[PDB]
Length: 114
Length: 114
Length: 114
Ligand SMILES: O=c1ccc2cc(O)c(O)cc2o1
Ligand SMILES: [Cl-]
Ligand SMILES: [Cl-]
Ligand SMILES: [Cl-]
Ligand SMILES: [Cl-]
Ligand SMILES: [Cl-]
Ligand SMILES: [Cl-]
Ligand SMILES: [Cl-]
Ligand SMILES: [Cl-]
Image 1 (cartoon, protein in one colour):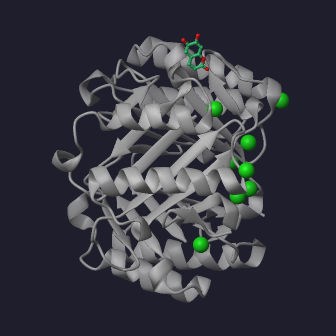
Image 2 (spheres, rainbow over the protein chains, first blue to last red):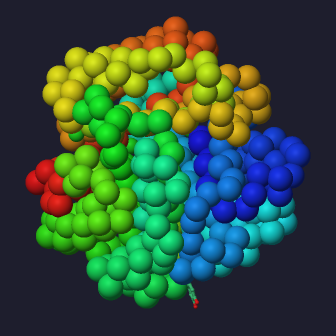
């Protein structure tokens, strides 16, 4: 899976070890091996949420499977909790788009997962 | 909904009020309340469009519904118009990908919209 | 089509002419005119792959058609090869997500491709 967070919070406010925490928590939540988890955090962005530039985040999670109604509710609670605790972003200022990718549409290591 | 614009135009050429204009115009165009509109502008990017690096933009609009043939033509006229007027990007150097998101695949506030 | 690469490799390691190489190689690979190929390279990112901060890349290719099982395997070999040769990123530290876009969902030049 791949998790991306774009935020207006400054880089210096992203704590040390945040990418590793995201990797470990996503491996556990999605069931996927840590080897297959990629994470990307983009601070210092020019963004607004509801017209306000108070701290906010726009995120995405792409995964081959492990996406669905109940699972995405669970991921949203986990990820909003991490963003609130570590980046001090209110959960009502976070969107996370979820994508269930077909294995044929994910390239890796000179091939695809199909 | 969420609107993202990535552009090679420099940050100093993004005028004051641009995120607010996008928020308000997208609220009107999508019919969704502005409280629900998130916007993200990414200037100074390393980009080419058709092999050249005159001003260009790559954008996306994600929305739960309010996406379709006619609506997307209307969004493109509105958004290209704003990028031309405010960022001086020619409409023929803009791509906007549209995504009609299922409510279960949009997280917010510790849950999803489903 | 649109190709985006996000990577932790530094900007100075992206060779001169890389955007043009991606444009031309993608025009050939997809069969589409170079005028329609847009490319975006984002270096210096805060990213991890498999928990590791060694060089990695997260990429996407969006195209109206020219996406499928065999084509995506061929694109992945081409693109991993370019990232390995030009950016020194190991292919097993690259993801590429592929998207077959409906023409009605790709805006351009005040309208869509539909
Ligand atoms: O999904 C959303 C996004 C923003 C938002 C803002 C509000 O003030 C509210 O009452 C509900 C909301 O729901
Ligand atoms: Cl995956
Ligand atoms: Cl589920
Ligand atoms: Cl897919
Ligand atoms: Cl929405
Ligand atoms: Cl429509
Ligand atoms: Cl969806
Ligand atoms: Cl295309
Ligand atoms: Cl589509």
